[PDB]
Length: 341
Ligand code: NI
Image (cartoon, rainbow, N blue to C red):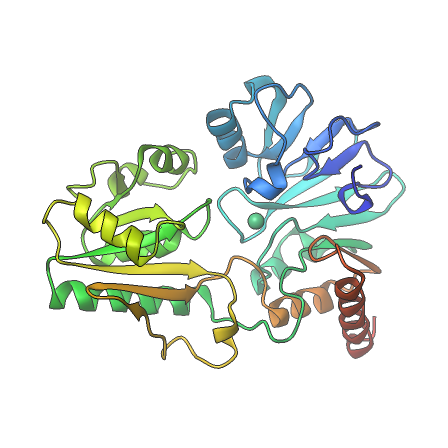
């Protein structure tokens, strides 16, 4: 049965709740972003409205094959009526097409659902700046003070440097980047740009990227592997046995791979900075971990919540154990006492 933190009070609306069958009373199913935990359940056979962003809509049509009529894309930053309830979609600064949703209830309550987000100060000068938010449904993925990680711009800097050094040292080396969902496209697009290349990838990955409304995308990507010296592979495949296997296929065209694994947090964030990173090495193949995050650090989350001063907070991540729930509430109480709301 659909959990209460996926339902919006005083509406027929649910959020990211596609895996339970029909939910009784639900006139509308909102989808925050195209990640499989959030969409798990959709198919071609859905005949209830789905409201989502334009970009999420393209992925729904082309990757899952939902029928154009049931996909209601909405533009961002635009006051929109949806069954006589005003709603707004806002950029979540997560993956392509990811949004947060502002719900304006008939009774006067205002609810923000963040979906998955990486909180940022530019959100403090959006339509949120204009009025009070009573209830916050919050992405709590990294709600604990151990979780620090660098800025996205810091990480992209490091990457543009590593890659370009190597390629200029050895002109027969390949850059590989790992992937398993949408998100983090900046890693590979930045590397390719510095190297004067398109990015090469499988047919299915190319299809997915062609749904994202990236400007100039035809100039940036290709399915011709031979012609490219930045390749994307499955994240499963980013290891030595798999990279050897792949290094064979290229047919004596490169004599060294240099790979990047964009990851979330790992325990090596506790004791090692970004300028002081190293790879594992089994012969000519070198694998970097780079902590490029599309979720809020603890500090970024904390600042966003203390600015918003919500009357109530409902976590949507790490809610499956009493210990995590209890740990999170304690942080929420500190934040509230510090900030005086
Ligand atoms: Ni996500």
